[PDB]
Amino acid sequence: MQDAITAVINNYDVQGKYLDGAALDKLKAYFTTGAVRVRAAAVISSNATTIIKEAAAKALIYSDLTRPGGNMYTTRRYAACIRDMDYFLRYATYAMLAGDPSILDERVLNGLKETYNSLGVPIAATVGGIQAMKEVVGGLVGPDAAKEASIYFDYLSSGLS
Amino acid sequence: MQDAITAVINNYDVQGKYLDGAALDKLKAYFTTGAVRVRAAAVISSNATTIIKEAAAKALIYSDLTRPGGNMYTTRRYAACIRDMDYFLRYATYAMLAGDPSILDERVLNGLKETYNSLGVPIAATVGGIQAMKEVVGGLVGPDAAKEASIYFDYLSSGLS
Amino acid sequence: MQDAITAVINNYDVQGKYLDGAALDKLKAYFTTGAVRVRAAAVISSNATTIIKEAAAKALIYSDLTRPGGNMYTTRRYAACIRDMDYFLRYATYAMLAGDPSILDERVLNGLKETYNSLGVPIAATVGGIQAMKEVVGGLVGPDAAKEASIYFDYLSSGLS
Amino acid sequence: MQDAITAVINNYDVQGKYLDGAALDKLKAYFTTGAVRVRAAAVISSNATTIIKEAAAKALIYSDLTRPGGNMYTTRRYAACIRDMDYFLRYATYAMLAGDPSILDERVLNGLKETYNSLGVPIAATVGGIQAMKEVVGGLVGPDAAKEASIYFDYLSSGLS
Amino acid sequence: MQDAITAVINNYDVQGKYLDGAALDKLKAYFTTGAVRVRAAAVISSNATTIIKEAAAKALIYSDLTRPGGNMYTTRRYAACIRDMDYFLRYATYAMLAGDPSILDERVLNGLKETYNSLGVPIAATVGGIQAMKEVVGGLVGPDAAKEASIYFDYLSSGLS
Amino acid sequence: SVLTKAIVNADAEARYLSPGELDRIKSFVASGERRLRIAQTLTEARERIVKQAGDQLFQIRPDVVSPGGNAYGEKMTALCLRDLDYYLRLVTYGIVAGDVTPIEEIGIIGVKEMYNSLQTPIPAVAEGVRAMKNVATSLLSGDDAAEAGFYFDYLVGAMQ
Amino acid sequence: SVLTKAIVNADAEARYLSPGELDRIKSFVASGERRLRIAQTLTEARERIVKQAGDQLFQIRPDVVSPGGNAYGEKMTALCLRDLDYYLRLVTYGIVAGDVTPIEEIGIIGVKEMYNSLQTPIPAVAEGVRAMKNVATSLLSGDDAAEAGFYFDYLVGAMQ
Amino acid sequence: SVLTKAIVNADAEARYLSPGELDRIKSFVASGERRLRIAQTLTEARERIVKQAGDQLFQIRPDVVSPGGNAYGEKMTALCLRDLDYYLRLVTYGIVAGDVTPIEEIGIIGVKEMYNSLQTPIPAVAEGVRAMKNVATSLLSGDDAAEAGFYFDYLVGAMQ
Amino acid sequence: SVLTKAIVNADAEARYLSPGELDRIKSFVASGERRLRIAQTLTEARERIVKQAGDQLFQIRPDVVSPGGNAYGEKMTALCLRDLDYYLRLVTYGIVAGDVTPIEEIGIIGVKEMYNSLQTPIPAVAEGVRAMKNVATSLLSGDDAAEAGFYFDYLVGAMQ
Amino acid sequence: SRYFKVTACIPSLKRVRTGRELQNTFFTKLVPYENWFTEQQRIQKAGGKVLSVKLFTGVQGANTGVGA
Amino acid sequence: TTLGPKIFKLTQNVGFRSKGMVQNAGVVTVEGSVQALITAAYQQIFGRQLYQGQRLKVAEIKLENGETTVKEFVRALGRSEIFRKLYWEPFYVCKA
Ligand SMILES: CCC1=C(C)/C(=C/C2=NC(=C\c3[nH]c(/C=C4\NC(=O)[C@H](C)[C@H]4CC)c(C)c3CCC(=O)O)/C(CCC(=O)O)=C2C)NC1=O
Ligand SMILES: CCC1=C(C)/C(=C/C2=NC(=C\c3[nH]c(/C=C4\NC(=O)[C@H](C)[C@H]4CC)c(C)c3CCC(=O)O)/C(CCC(=O)O)=C2C)NC1=O
Ligand SMILES: CCC1=C(C)/C(=C/C2=NC(=C\c3[nH]c(/C=C4\NC(=O)[C@H](C)[C@H]4CC)c(C)c3CCC(=O)O)/C(CCC(=O)O)=C2C)NC1=O
Ligand SMILES: CCC1=C(C)/C(=C/C2=NC(=C\c3[nH]c(/C=C4\NC(=O)[C@H](C)[C@H]4CC)c(C)c3CCC(=O)O)/C(CCC(=O)O)=C2C)NC1=O
Ligand SMILES: CCC1=C(C)/C(=C/C2=NC(=C\c3[nH]c(/C=C4\NC(=O)[C@H](C)[C@H]4CC)c(C)c3CCC(=O)O)/C(CCC(=O)O)=C2C)NC1=O
Ligand SMILES: CCC1=C(C)/C(=C/C2=NC(=C\c3[nH]c(/C=C4\NC(=O)[C@H](C)[C@H]4CC)c(C)c3CCC(=O)O)/C(CCC(=O)O)=C2C)NC1=O
Ligand SMILES: CCC1=C(C)/C(=C/C2=NC(=C\c3[nH]c(/C=C4\NC(=O)[C@H](C)[C@H]4CC)c(C)c3CCC(=O)O)/C(CCC(=O)O)=C2C)NC1=O
Ligand SMILES: CCC1=C(C)/C(=C/C2=NC(=C\c3[nH]c(/C=C4\NC(=O)[C@H](C)[C@H]4CC)c(C)c3CCC(=O)O)/C(CCC(=O)O)=C2C)NC1=O
Ligand SMILES: CCC1=C(C)/C(=C/C2=NC(=C\c3[nH]c(/C=C4\NC(=O)[C@H](C)[C@H]4CC)c(C)c3CCC(=O)O)/C(CCC(=O)O)=C2C)NC1=O
């Protein structure tokens, strides 16, 4: 994986360049937002379970999805689905701390679209589950962090569609 | 895998034939070159490291390959490349002892072309690394063994291209 | 480990004897109590968790054992202890079905006394945990099965002391 | 394995005591020496190889130990011995950072005396190898850290004798 | 393991001595008996099964050992016992070829006394099984080899008692 | 601690500590006296924090102190504030260590079984800890209150 | 970085980041501005550091620039200083990130095998790095010189 | 062969051949012409060797060639000698290879299952092979007869 | 030896020696007197060989015996020839054993770690051994010189 | 981090091993604390006998410091 | 059979057996059969050998000294550091 900082280091390493003014400006733009990323992660982590619960309630359950014939019918599959939800939330929190989406590609999106096609897992319904968790997250983390958390949920959801 | 001798045995076994004159002539043609194969292997094995170093020096390093942007840039990848080189040398030595290239297909070439395409490993540059080790080998092993060692390096290199 | 039917078969097989009226009488004495053993097992299995809970409540917790300095202090230790309790209950249920204590020796008691000495696990306190589960079991299974279940709990507890 | 901060907590936990004034004074006595421990570790780590070399030169080699019949005769055993030396140095550096010798017992001394008796490894000679590395270490780390590094080398050496 | 020849080489290596007259005399004393060792091994190997059968017949079966209560009662244990016998015969043949008992210690005797105590395997009865195979072996191999084969059977049997 | 967590990485790769690892030990230890002050203040007000936590928590979810509630009665309740006293303590052993290893060995390892076995309602319990946050946090400066708050929210997180 | 290292340990455990590892990051952020500044300073004097390192090296070990020496001759010396320029660059990277991370992948893992092939004496490369420490360190304030020095001593350590 | 066996062990331990492995290849190849002569003699007398094995077999077991026997009849006997011809062929292969790899894959692995299906008495096939040893061995010098005999006794061994 | 190697493989597969294994013991023992003569000649000239190899090692590597060289000085050179005397001795052992078991346990397993500690350049030790091959080989008949040469090239191989 | 010391006799009644299985039946080995329960039971289930148990590495009722 | 790959089983005592041999014997012998087992562990678990820093000693030291079995040497290697790193970390979770 890479973060903001190693994204820059590797981009310069392939050119064998010492870090110059443009590089140093990018890294500053990361460091200057760093404390806010940490606070936001502590809110998400400590509200993890409630975010999933409120996101499922707005976007998944009370529906045909949870009824016989639906993909989140059976305690087995309901458990698998909210298990997935926890992955998304947790990794988006990593991406936002790192200030780089590369981890969402390497460890979450790669092959996932076809995995879901192969099992029958409804993609559009999963995206709504992602964009509902974003909605909840953006309330809990506040002005400071709302836009920055949000983008990695949006990265996740355009990665499936 | 198979060698000269088992190549003949299996070719006759599928016909259920006892070994006949033509078979016996082939096996003789192997046994009669056997002592020379052994001596050649002992030269290659004991000069292994020097062959790689002289082959890399003529065909790989002092170049864009070892510079930033090049596939053998980074100590990691330089190490992986000369590691590979040792495989080639070592297996070619097996093929030449066996007097059969089948091991080069089973344990070296199978899937390797696409593996290199997938990682970005430069094929043409790797072939030159093979044909440089051949050049060195042919000097070290002498008249007796030069042609016989050479062919399995040539087998390796037309297996990639 | 053997059952009841082959603990008699092995007693007569280290003699060369056949099955003599005496043998057949023993086996009858087992078969004739068999149906009663089966439910009793169905009561224990289906009340497993409640038996442990009531046995711990009468004989382990609300005490120095669960307080700092006590062996079942820490969630890790408390979990290990009631895990053990489940083993005892479960195996005693096997012994009682088999009508033979040999499984309690082979798979539970062997080395356990010294294992507990080595970790510091309080033996006397563990016996009370066994004899409390027996008390609960004897109520739940009824007149039919009370004495028969009870003995394998008593086997367990004199195996430690 | 535990340290000074951790030991204070466990030592009080078994008594179920809040940290009180006496505890808080102990922890201060650790924190107040902490920066010096770090600097000392960076000197030892970065001079690791030279310390072993100078310690072996003063206390092991140029001797019957390295001659036929000696335990550090053969490149195999010479390698094993200075391998060991590196363990000692490295772990003593851990003990000194932690401000607690418990790791030296758990991961180094336990069974080592008898292991050395069983292989024939000379104990007295190994102690001199420890006390020579201490001598070198105490020069390199300076007034600040000399006494504190020294004690865990002395812990090691009275652990063998 | 070691044989006659490597016994001498390692005894001199630890002193870093080139082989001298005394060493050279020892090695001659081995080489000069070598052809006879080979012939003896070919007799033992090719009569292996008959030696075990005649040794068991004189020293094990037709007894309480093979009756209920006996350690070689059951086809399982009878099989294990003559399996063992084959080990002894086979390894003694190795020791005698090597002209060194070290293999009998490394791969046969180490821990075996206690293994037999732990299973209940009768030691004295096993020794008689060894000394009966020796008796048979000494007839089959003849004057040339009788004394030399015999000693490694005697090594085996005083290794258990 | 930070030491325990980190050295473990050193030993596992058979090596001395990195410049990075050394730096964090240095920054960590510099933040010592403050962490010790945060633990002292909270140790000094433990009885108040527990008691006021106990009043607060039976508003946000009372049912636990009712006929069919796990904490119904005087001694089912008192074992309840004592558990709240336990967790506040752990929130302070951990504060001086600068990480969770000590807390974890003594309290969140295999803690979802004690409770499941006891059928104490665990998720109410997380709420119980968040409340020791509200009281404790009102006895600390803004900066110290946040630093403390992370450890309260961890426990709340682990009971989940 | 410090970030990468913290996270990788977090994800391996599959639980959100702690308190004790959500701190170090804060220290690093404050440190990073200073860290970025030190790297820039080192970058400015690179040619002087390399050249003076190269003189200090060849006095201390004249054998490498002698008949049977790996660096004997005008080029064989040119490539040698270029390698010294490489490692100074990696040292600036390490300082800025706050964790050594990328430098390891770029220039120590595989370095034994590379230099053994080329027949380069490894311990005299370690000396060239000490020589650079001495020069670079004389262009930095006491506090910044120490912070830089840890990364120089790491490279010296890894070539071992 | 001896080659295949040596190499497979080499490659599986990721290494070049041992002095031992090299020595046996050398001793083996020196016996090449001799081994080829042993195969030639036996190939040259194949038809004789099968009829004398076949006579030796039917005396010792007249039952196999009896009402309830697997080889009862003219064409149940014809197939039986053909199987004896198969195994003599494999024995010539083994002798020139210097081990059983070829003999094994072609005619022992799976042989229990094959013959159990056909309900052929395996141990009387082993006898047919002993019978061939006796005939073949009478057409070879003492030294060559022993070398051949090992491969006959192997097949006899594998049908067991 | 050849014996030890054959047997260890036999015992490890729980079996008597193979025809192959028996053959190599026979060929080996037939070369006994010859192998003993090869060791005698070389033992008899051990001084000549070690000194000469040192002059030739120090010609291709003049700096080992130079300011920053491992063998620089009169007693750093004395120990260097003593090591050359050690390896010639082990080569005589190997020749009479017919394999490397003894050579290996005594002087290659652990040799990288030993010399890395002493900071001895390994590949120039390999050169010292080639130099000894050249001298020793000039005191032996063509056939015996080759047989000896395999063991010299092995040591050269193992220091790699 | 704690380790156990262990002694056990593992016996195979019906499998039948030809060569050298003496290491195979009786052995002493160090096992970690977290794998002991499973190891112990791997041994009871195949008829083995456990001669002794050694911590080797821990302390008896250590509340902290134990950890994995 | 010979139709599949070799199986290495460490029967060779190991154990630091000792004997009736010279106290500081040079040749020792057969503590080189363990060594091939040790490299063959690496060749299954990672597929190749590791580089110099990488190998896990002090797991081998114990296997070689006879203190732990083959089974536990595999466990140490499996749960190790570079094993995680090479094979877990860079891939999608189920590919890993
Ligand atoms: C056939 C397998 C299967 C089961 C059993 C199942 C249960 C299930 N129970 C639910 C809610 C619920 N279930 C209960 C049940 C109870 N409340 C209590 O206190 C009592 C202990 C218990 C009644 C005995 C309650 C109160 C909710 C609402 C919880 C909420 O909305 O947060 C929901 C979410 C609402 C929905 O979308 O349907 C599911 C999926 N789903 C399944 O696929
Ligand atoms: C670490 C990164 C990672 C991710 C994200 C991941 C996803 C993932 N989801 C899976 C299944 C699944 N995923 C879901 C998800 C859902 N069901 C619905 O109806 C909703 C639309 C949605 C939840 C919002 C369900 C129901 C299954 C079970 C399919 C089955 O029954 O086989 C599986 C198959 C294996 C298994 O069942 O566990 C994987 C690998 N695996 C990974 O390694
Ligand atoms: C960023 C990671 C990285 C490094 C460090 C690296 C080093 C590196 N050093 C090289 C050569 C060299 N390096 C040196 C260095 C030295 N000679 C000495 O004696 C001294 C000990 C030392 C100088 C301090 C010399 C003399 C050569 C030429 C060797 C030859 O051509 O045989 C080469 C081959 C030439 C080339 O193609 O560039 C590489 C790739 N490559 C990399 O990708
Ligand atoms: C036993 C038979 C066998 C072979 C031959 C083999 C080759 C092989 N080469 C690899 C990578 C590689 N191979 C090279 C090779 C080179 N780089 C260059 O620029 C040169 C042209 C060339 C050397 C002459 C490099 C640089 C990589 C690393 C690619 C990466 O960074 O992922 C990998 C990927 C896994 C790994 O990194 O180790 C394999 C499997 N694997 C095998 O199992
Ligand atoms: C330091 C680690 C640690 C903890 C935390 C711990 C808790 C613990 N809580 C207990 C009981 C209890 N704990 C509670 C707690 C509650 N009731 C509720 O409804 C609320 C949700 C909650 C209060 C916030 C109650 C009511 C009992 C009595 C349950 C019973 O007796 O059945 C007991 C059994 C009584 C005893 O023997 O002490 C233990 C061991 N033990 C430990 O070693
Ligand atoms: C299948 C048969 C079987 C049994 C029965 C078994 C028992 C057993 N109990 C253990 C520990 C333990 N056992 C207890 C038990 C108790 N603590 C108390 O205070 C009470 C008196 C008692 C519960 C009533 C505790 C607390 C430990 C943990 C000791 C430690 O911290 O290391 C361990 C050590 C490994 C581990 O921690 O899991 C074993 C093997 N193992 C088995 O394989
Ligand atoms: C029989 C198995 C065996 C070997 C081979 C062995 C070698 C060995 N070589 C040593 C030193 C040495 N060896 C050398 C050798 C060399 N310097 C070079 O540059 C060349 C590459 C090479 C000569 C060809 C040097 C220079 C030293 C001194 C290193 C020092 O003191 O730091 C030492 C330490 C000094 C001592 O106490 O004896 C040992 C033990 N020990 C053994 O038990
Ligand atoms: C992580 C903690 C740890 C330590 C400390 C450790 C020591 C240790 N030293 C050993 C052997 C040894 N240790 C030495 C040490 C010495 N020789 C001398 O003459 C000197 C007096 C001394 C060096 C100063 C030697 C020579 C051997 C090899 C014995 C043999 O040939 O079997 C062995 C046997 C396995 C092996 O050979 O690697 C162990 C386990 N193992 C561990 O896991
Ligand atoms: C390669 C070297 C080697 C040896 C020698 C060896 C012996 C050995 N004998 C065993 C058992 C045994 N050994 C015997 C032997 C005998 N019974 C008698 O009554 C007679 C006195 C005697 C035969 C003469 C029997 C009966 C058993 C089975 C014990 C049981 O039932 O568990 C076992 C236990 C595992 C097993 O059952 O296979 C071993 C390891 N193992 C080895 O690895």
Image (spheres, coloured by chain):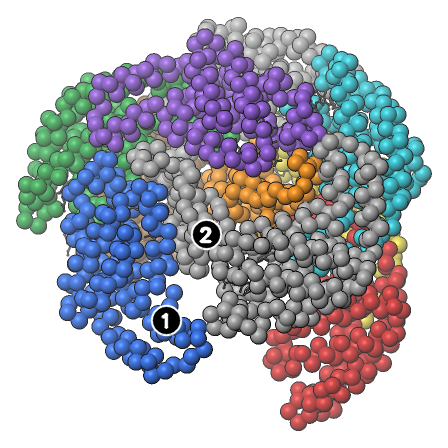
Chain colours: A brown, B yellow, C blue, D purple, F green, H red, I cyan, K orange
- In the figure, is residue I15 to the left or right of K13? right
Q: Nearer the viewer, residue F144 or F41?
A: F41
Q: Amino acid at mark 2?
A: Ala
Q: Is residue D76 visible?
A: yes
Q: Where does the image place residue A2, in percent across and percent down from the top left?
A: 46, 31
| Marked residue chain, label 1 | C
Determine crowd level at label 2: few under 14, some 14-19, many 20+ residues with C-alpha closer than 10 A: many
The residue at which mark 2 appears reads as J8
| Residue beneath disc 1 | C7
Q: How many marks?
A: 2
Q: Is residue I26 found left or right of K76 in the rendered image?
A: right
Residue at 25% across / 78% down in the picture?
C32
**On screen, residue I98 above or below C96:** above
Most foreground residue, B146 or B37: B37
Hey, which quadrant is residue F73 in on the image? Answer: top left
Percent x, y for residue H49? 83, 79
Is any part of residue B91 visible from this angle? no
The one nearer the camera, D113 or I136, is: D113
